[PDB]
Image 1 (cartoon, rainbow, N blue to C red):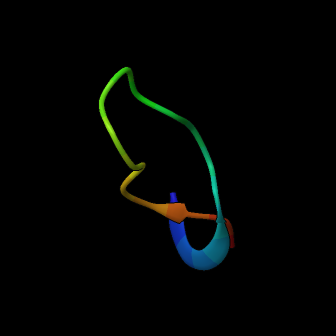
Image 2 (cartoon, helix red, strand yellow):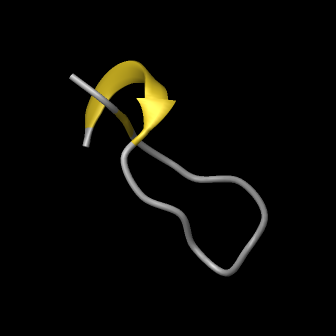
Length: 21
């Protein structure tokens, strides 16, 4: 959700969008 370094969730696509924090 935030703009951190580790993803919050994963989609059935390629890469995730938002990050922790």
